[PDB]
Length: 89
Length: 89
Image (cartoon, rainbow over all chains, first blue to last red; front, side):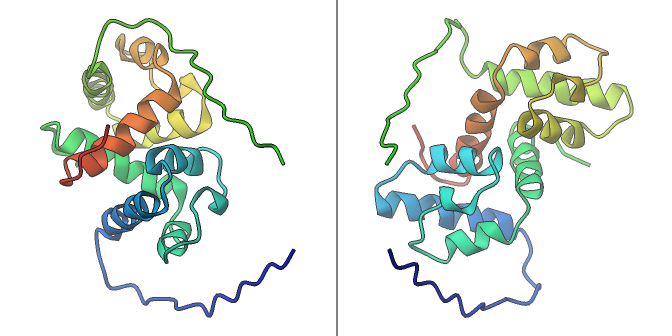
């Protein structure tokens, strides 16, 4: 084998907001491009806690990894009820 | 080296659809009546697999419990991107 991985570490400074929304948008498309099942890998990622659920195609794997699966899931739950007509406090 | 498709097909017969959406609506209402934060308790339920995360005020705790955490979580994931302008199956 040859695990060649050098993540230079971009580390974007916090300034953006609602980033989780762009993160999953990106992650979703990443698997669409790679021919995988985005939903299946995302659901598996949050409730199993392992970065390898998201294929290393795009910075998406890093983006999702820089957010807590707890945090992301809260956002999922909030949005679910929000567009369902509920304003979350 | 463990190339195994795991489509369990353990699909239990349920006659409802979009019920999860109605269920979380119920659960959300349940915590507001109890003076808690609906999101905090729901997020814990799905990723911990512990029914005790939902307070026992209303039938909501029973309703959510009839649904698998995975089932709801995938629905959350799809819906998140769906109303975001993405069409998911």
